[PDB]
Amino acid sequence: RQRFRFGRLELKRISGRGFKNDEEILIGNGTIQKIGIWDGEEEFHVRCGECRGILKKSKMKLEKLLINSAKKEDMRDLIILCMVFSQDTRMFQGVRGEINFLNRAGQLLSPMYQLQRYFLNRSSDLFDQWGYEESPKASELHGINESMNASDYTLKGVVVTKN
Ligand SMILES: Nc1nc2c(ncn2[C@@H]2O[C@H](COP(=O)(O)OP(=O)(O)O)[C@@H](O)[C@H]2O)c(=O)[nH]1
Image (cartoon, rainbow, N blue to C red; front, side, top):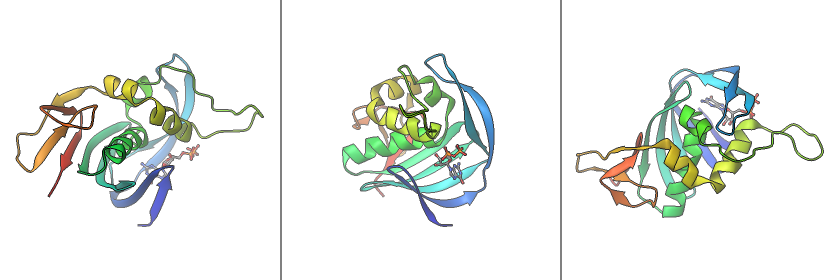
Protein backbone atom coordinates (compact mmCIF):
# COMPACT_ATOMS: atom_id res chain seq x y z
CA ARG A 1 0.00 0.00 0.00
CA GLN A 2 2.04 2.89 -1.38
CA ARG A 3 1.36 6.63 -1.31
CA PHE A 4 0.46 7.72 -4.84
CA ARG A 5 -0.63 10.98 -6.44
CA PHE A 6 -3.61 12.17 -8.46
CA GLY A 7 -2.54 15.73 -9.21
CA ARG A 8 -2.94 17.73 -6.01
CA LEU A 9 -4.52 14.69 -4.36
CA GLU A 10 -2.39 12.24 -2.40
CA LEU A 11 -3.78 8.78 -1.66
CA LYS A 12 -2.86 5.71 0.37
CA ARG A 13 -5.00 2.57 0.13
CA ILE A 14 -6.71 1.29 3.28
CA SER A 15 -8.72 -1.61 1.85
CA GLY A 16 -10.40 -2.93 -1.28
CA ARG A 17 -9.30 -3.45 -4.87
CA GLY A 18 -10.59 -1.77 -8.02
CA PHE A 19 -10.86 -3.08 -11.57
CA LYS A 20 -10.71 -0.56 -14.41
CA ASN A 21 -12.85 -0.86 -17.54
CA ASP A 22 -13.14 1.65 -20.39
CA GLU A 23 -16.68 3.00 -20.68
CA GLU A 24 -18.40 5.67 -22.76
CA ILE A 25 -19.43 8.42 -20.35
CA LEU A 26 -22.03 11.06 -21.20
CA ILE A 27 -20.68 14.09 -19.35
CA GLY A 28 -22.68 17.21 -18.56
CA ASN A 29 -21.80 19.28 -21.63
CA GLY A 30 -23.53 16.76 -23.89
CA THR A 31 -20.35 15.12 -25.18
CA ILE A 32 -19.48 11.44 -24.84
CA GLN A 33 -15.94 10.50 -23.80
CA LYS A 34 -14.38 7.09 -23.22
CA ILE A 35 -13.05 6.97 -19.66
CA GLY A 36 -11.43 4.22 -17.60
CA ILE A 37 -14.04 3.43 -14.96
CA TRP A 38 -12.95 1.73 -11.73
CA ASP A 39 -15.23 -1.01 -10.40
CA GLY A 40 -15.19 -2.25 -6.82
CA GLU A 41 -15.27 -0.92 -3.27
CA GLU A 42 -12.13 0.97 -2.27
CA GLU A 43 -11.00 2.94 0.79
CA PHE A 44 -8.16 5.47 0.92
CA HIS A 45 -6.24 7.82 3.15
CA VAL A 46 -6.48 11.10 1.25
CA ARG A 47 -4.65 14.41 1.58
CA CYS A 48 -4.69 17.83 -0.05
CA GLY A 49 -2.26 20.25 1.56
CA GLU A 50 -2.90 20.37 5.30
CA CYS A 51 -6.26 18.62 5.08
CA ARG A 52 -6.32 14.93 5.98
CA GLY A 53 -9.18 12.59 5.10
CA ILE A 54 -10.66 9.16 4.43
CA LEU A 55 -12.35 8.40 1.11
CA LYS A 56 -14.71 5.49 0.46
CA LYS A 57 -15.94 4.75 -3.06
CA SER A 58 -17.63 2.19 -5.29
CA LYS A 59 -18.20 2.09 -9.05
CA MET A 60 -18.88 5.69 -10.10
CA LYS A 61 -19.96 6.74 -6.61
CA LEU A 62 -18.48 8.51 -3.61
CA GLU A 63 -19.74 6.42 -0.69
CA LYS A 64 -18.35 8.62 2.08
CA LEU A 65 -15.74 11.31 2.72
CA LEU A 66 -14.39 11.86 6.24
CA ILE A 67 -12.23 14.99 6.42
CA ASN A 68 -10.55 16.84 9.27
CA SER A 69 -10.97 20.52 10.09
CA ALA A 70 -8.16 22.49 8.47
CA LYS A 71 -7.42 25.37 6.11
CA LYS A 72 -10.68 26.07 4.26
CA GLU A 73 -8.85 26.26 0.93
CA ASP A 74 -7.45 22.77 1.52
CA MET A 75 -10.76 21.39 2.78
CA ARG A 76 -12.48 22.65 -0.37
CA ASP A 77 -9.89 21.31 -2.80
CA LEU A 78 -9.71 17.93 -1.05
CA ILE A 79 -13.47 17.60 -1.45
CA ILE A 80 -13.22 18.57 -5.12
CA LEU A 81 -10.41 16.11 -5.82
CA CYS A 82 -12.20 13.28 -4.00
CA MET A 83 -15.40 13.99 -5.93
CA VAL A 84 -13.49 13.69 -9.20
CA PHE A 85 -11.41 10.68 -8.10
CA SER A 86 -14.57 8.85 -7.02
CA GLN A 87 -15.80 9.18 -10.63
CA ASP A 88 -19.27 9.86 -9.22
CA THR A 89 -22.07 10.25 -11.76
CA ARG A 90 -22.96 13.65 -10.29
CA MET A 91 -19.39 14.79 -10.95
CA PHE A 92 -19.56 13.94 -14.66
CA GLN A 93 -22.92 15.74 -14.82
CA GLY A 94 -21.33 18.85 -13.34
CA VAL A 95 -19.26 19.54 -16.46
CA ARG A 96 -21.12 22.43 -18.09
CA GLY A 97 -18.26 24.04 -20.00
CA GLU A 98 -15.75 22.80 -22.55
CA ILE A 99 -13.07 20.24 -21.68
CA ASN A 100 -10.31 19.29 -24.11
CA PHE A 101 -8.88 15.77 -24.00
CA LEU A 102 -6.36 16.80 -26.65
CA ASN A 103 -3.98 19.76 -26.51
CA ARG A 104 -3.41 22.12 -29.45
CA ALA A 105 -0.56 19.93 -30.68
CA GLY A 106 -2.99 17.02 -30.89
CA GLN A 107 -1.39 15.07 -28.05
CA LEU A 108 -3.35 12.71 -25.79
CA LEU A 109 -4.53 14.07 -22.44
CA SER A 110 -5.77 12.17 -19.39
CA PRO A 111 -9.58 12.50 -19.11
CA MET A 112 -9.48 12.14 -15.32
CA TYR A 113 -6.68 14.69 -14.96
CA GLN A 114 -8.50 17.14 -17.23
CA LEU A 115 -11.57 16.74 -15.02
CA GLN A 116 -9.43 17.64 -12.01
CA ARG A 117 -8.14 20.81 -13.68
CA TYR A 118 -11.69 21.73 -14.68
CA PHE A 119 -13.40 21.33 -11.31
CA LEU A 120 -10.56 22.92 -9.35
CA ASN A 121 -11.64 26.03 -11.24
CA ARG A 122 -15.38 25.26 -11.30
CA SER A 123 -16.19 24.22 -7.72
CA SER A 124 -19.50 26.09 -7.49
CA ASP A 125 -20.96 24.22 -10.47
CA LEU A 126 -19.77 20.94 -8.95
CA PHE A 127 -21.21 21.60 -5.49
CA ASP A 128 -24.58 22.75 -6.86
CA GLN A 129 -24.85 19.64 -9.04
CA TRP A 130 -23.60 17.40 -6.23
CA GLY A 131 -26.51 18.27 -3.95
CA TYR A 132 -26.85 18.49 -0.18
CA GLU A 133 -28.22 16.39 2.67
CA GLU A 134 -28.96 16.59 6.40
CA SER A 135 -25.86 17.10 8.55
CA PRO A 136 -25.06 14.33 11.08
CA LYS A 137 -26.80 14.64 14.46
CA ALA A 138 -23.73 13.20 16.20
CA SER A 139 -21.70 15.68 18.25
CA GLU A 140 -18.30 14.49 17.02
CA LEU A 141 -19.36 14.96 13.39
CA HIS A 142 -20.41 18.22 11.71
CA GLY A 143 -21.72 19.14 8.27
CA ILE A 144 -20.13 21.46 5.74
CA ASN A 145 -21.56 23.70 3.02
CA GLU A 146 -20.25 25.22 -0.21
CA SER A 147 -18.58 27.99 1.79
CA MET A 148 -16.65 25.39 3.81
CA ASN A 149 -18.54 26.46 6.94
CA ALA A 150 -20.32 24.45 9.62
CA SER A 151 -23.92 24.05 8.47
CA ASP A 152 -27.17 22.20 9.15
CA TYR A 153 -26.88 20.83 5.62
CA THR A 154 -23.79 19.16 4.17
CA LEU A 155 -22.42 18.06 0.81
CA LYS A 156 -23.72 14.53 0.19
CA GLY A 157 -21.38 11.89 1.60
CA VAL A 158 -19.14 14.51 3.20
CA VAL A 159 -18.77 15.01 6.94
CA VAL A 160 -16.10 16.97 8.79
CA THR A 161 -14.40 15.69 11.92
CA LYS A 162 -12.28 17.26 14.67
CA ASN A 163 -11.56 14.25 16.87
N1 LIG B 1 -10.24 3.78 -7.58
C1 LIG B 1 -8.95 3.70 -7.98
N2 LIG B 1 -8.49 4.66 -8.83
C2 LIG B 1 -7.21 4.63 -9.27
C3 LIG B 1 -6.31 3.56 -8.81
N3 LIG B 1 -5.12 3.78 -9.40
C4 LIG B 1 -5.24 4.90 -10.16
N4 LIG B 1 -6.48 5.41 -10.07
C5 LIG B 1 -7.01 6.60 -10.77
O1 LIG B 1 -7.36 6.24 -12.10
C6 LIG B 1 -7.06 7.30 -13.01
C7 LIG B 1 -6.24 6.74 -14.16
O2 LIG B 1 -6.56 7.45 -15.35
P1 LIG B 1 -5.42 7.71 -16.45
O3 LIG B 1 -4.16 8.22 -15.79
O4 LIG B 1 -5.90 8.68 -17.50
O5 LIG B 1 -5.17 6.24 -17.06
P2 LIG B 1 -6.18 5.59 -18.14
O6 LIG B 1 -7.48 5.25 -17.46
O7 LIG B 1 -5.56 4.32 -18.67
O8 LIG B 1 -6.42 6.55 -19.27
C8 LIG B 1 -6.25 8.32 -12.24
O9 LIG B 1 -7.04 9.49 -12.05
C9 LIG B 1 -5.96 7.69 -10.89
O10 LIG B 1 -6.09 8.67 -9.85
C10 LIG B 1 -6.89 2.56 -7.89
O11 LIG B 1 -6.20 1.62 -7.45
N5 LIG B 1 -8.17 2.70 -7.53
